Amino acid sequence: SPRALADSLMQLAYQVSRLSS
Amino acid sequence: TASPRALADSLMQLAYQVSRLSS
Amino acid sequence: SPRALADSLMQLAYQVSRLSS
Amino acid sequence: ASPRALADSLMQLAYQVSRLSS
């Protein structure tokens, strides 16, 4: 579902924000 | 390659758009 | 890992492409 | 934006994410 995919993308966005260059 | 912060901000904005799609 | 997150994102991108406007 | 366009953008972002570091 769109909502399930959006939830997953939001979680991944926060994880990506904790990476480094 | 963009920064982690810029990529995360982009992903967040896309996630909000995805949520408005339909099955 | 960046690779694992990127692979997850690619899978999600493909699923998004199969959604409807 | 269309599902196709959003998917293209997400794919582009995934390629970039793969070049980041832990």
Image (tube, coloured by chain):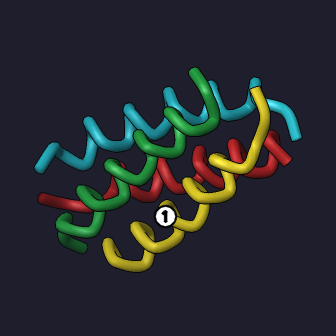
Chain colours: A red, B cyan, C yellow, D green
Q: Residue at x 59, y 49 (%)?
A: A9
Three-letter amino acid code of the residue under disc 1: Met
- Where on the picture, by quarter, is residue A10? top right
Direction from residue C16 to residue A15 in the image, left or right: left
Q: Position of residue D19 (x, y in %)?
A: 18, 67
Q: Which residue is drawn at 72% across and 50% down?
A: C18
Q: Position of residue C3 (x, y in %)?
A: 34, 77
Using the image, name the chain to which the residue with label 1 belongs. Answer: C
Q: Position of residue D4 (x, y in %)?
A: 56, 38
Q: How many marks?
A: 1
Direction from residue A16 to residue D20 in the image, left or right: left
| Position of A4 relative to C11 (above/below) | above
| Position of A12 relative to D20 (above/below) | above
**Closer to the camera in the image, A21 or B23:** B23
Quadrant showing the C terminus of chain D: bottom left
**Closer to the camera in the image, D12 or B16:** D12
Disc 1 target residue: C10
Mark 1 lies on a secondary structure that is helix
Q: Position of residue B8 (x, y in %)?
A: 38, 42
Q: Which residue is drawn at 68% across and 57% down?
A: C15
Quadrant showing the N terminus of chain D: top right
